[PDB]
Length: 6
Image (cartoon, rainbow, N blue to C red; front, top):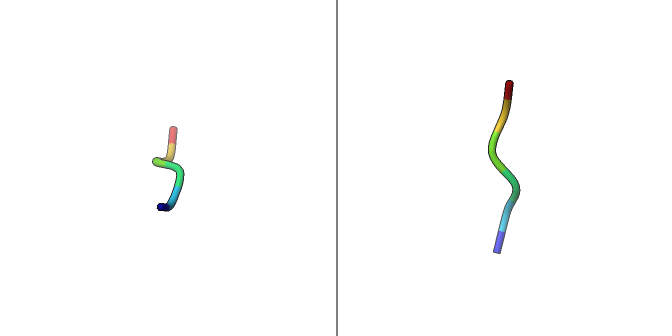
């Protein structure tokens, strides 16, 4: 899994 970005 990977985190999103802001």
